[PDB]
Image (cartoon, rainbow over the protein chains, first blue to last red):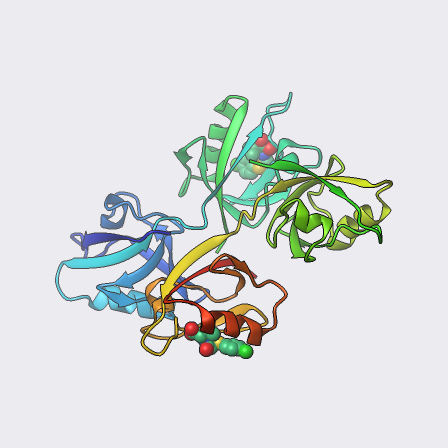
Length: 164
Length: 162
Ligand SMILES: CC(C)[C@H](NC(=O)CSc1ccc(Cl)cc1)C(=O)O
Ligand SMILES: CC(C)[C@H](NC(=O)CSc1ccc(Cl)cc1)C(=O)O
């Protein structure tokens, strides 16, 4: 909730590696490209953008935010950021079959299995998986998320966020 | 961390709770003033994990309400997660006494350009839960405006997605 400032420099192709999305008259980070200027200043999926070059993003369309970034004079772009403000952590325990009890697609939880640790702990659907046991899984394929869950110990801590 | 709470039904057999199904969970939509619910610390936005040791996962609002109504005895147990969607934003009134938002039915509907609300990233389609620690769930819009108009310069609002 406490804002922080980041300075980006456009790469060789003139890009910062960011897709922004207008939600509820705010601006949120929808995509950070691996190894991008955005990635290197710590921008993450679900970050809220309060200011671009000291101008308020309030009520901006996705297009406007993107036009402002594209037209930005010179190499140096400032953003005022709230770090993943809607991020929440839930702890589950694997059952005798090694399952916590949820289905997901494209890193979004789609159903909760009856009588599972996910059910007991009130895990929610229409939430994106951000981290498993402190490991960032944004941008991983579903099979890679399953690989991490399958190799986990009994305790599974998942960081979630309401989906875009 | 969830907590377990014990409610004793009032003289009418009620706990003073309205529940809502969201994202295959169950959430507190209303806590009646001075109700058994109120007295064990339940608030708008609390998540209900268990009622009498049964998982609420995937229950309709109706089912949660039927289970509460059918509960035999003086004593109802719930497992509660404290307001997991709760977000607090601090704003400062401008020279005209405004923070810079419009709301309707306790729900923020627009952010005024160049306002404290704009600078602080206040969001629309969010319900106002508290103003400076005071609960405003169930208040009429004009009563919410009265509280904002009476506030000091510092306005801390607790919001939640609608
Ligand atoms: C992986 C765990 C979350 C496990 N759940 C599932 O296997 C169903 S979800 C899934 C979806 C796409 C792929 Cl590629 C792999 C798994 C559990 O409930 O513990
Ligand atoms: C009330 C505050 C939030 C103030 N905002 C407004 O005057 C516009 S919103 C409003 C809606 C319904 C009623 Cl009945 C009264 C006011 C501000 O921007 O500080």
